[PDB]
Image 1 (cartoon, each protein chain N blue to C red):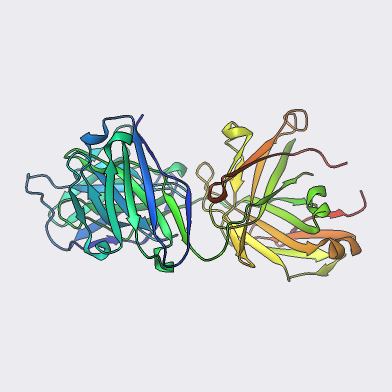
Image 2 (cartoon, rainbow over the protein chains, first blue to last red):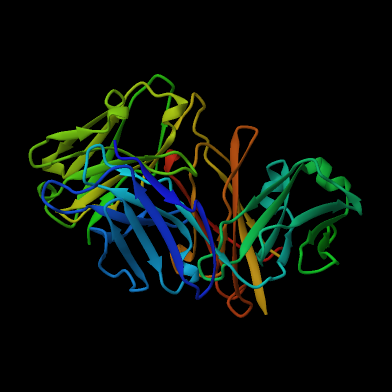
Length: 218
Length: 213
């Protein structure tokens, strides 16, 4: 079976830079018809993969020209000649010349860009959730860079770590930034005994945290 | 427009079987090989096999010989992959793809079916609005099983400014949320509605974000 090896597994690049990704096949990949069916696919976060290059070096319909593949024998290479945010995702080589057909393990293209502080927003539990007997407080820390960030919750000023669930997006396709949501989940009884709720964001962009808070009453 | 339509999700009991569907349109079904792929979440692609809808002849990756069976129904333009006695190792996205003749194995991909293998029942999400020169609004999609859910805003016409956060598992249920940022002259005077699809239970929920009072 054709073993396809990709390096690097992770590829950090600045916007506008060149990127180079290589794929090595453990044996030759010429199909009986003469054709070398080496393909490059790109899978963006959330999406199915999409064809970039076919037969080693041909651009698929409507693929931009900053993409080009090259190589021969067992060494194949994908160049992205001027990288942009929409290029984020995992790149895979693939050989279709021999059964069983096989994929490389993927190369993850990361964009490195200027730092950016988060835009933080806090949300009270909804009246619909309260009537139901639960109470979640949600905080968005949106469009920050780099991925590292800390959130801290406070109830009437006292630090609270139980029942907090955090989620980060993948790098954004327009922005190259990250976002995260943090959710403090309580019972309506617990929520209703205490008055002020605070979301604190600490990020490499400032020594002082961005603080966003509200009061149960109005 | 070549379309390969796959259901979003399938819930399966351990030991049971599924039959995954791939309905094709936008070209003559019998003209192109169909390929299938497995992707465990966050993990890299494997090639299961391919079938000629014209001749019904097949080739399998040995690894799947005894897990997967490919068939087609030419009259409905539909390709099928039957997976037998499921195990948590079978929980994964399964893609069908359309081969472009002597050119590439996956010129077009379906959206993929997320197969969760579990004994747990389906649970639909609760969907809650998050209300407070730019405004940020959101949707909290709470307490569902299995994955995935799909979120849009204003039926897809609000595309930019959106962050939909990967779900997190807790107490055996998933929770996700989405935020959208709009100019303050858009909301509250225009309606902003989040659209939640949870295919495993065929639920769709529209939730209008109204200002708190």
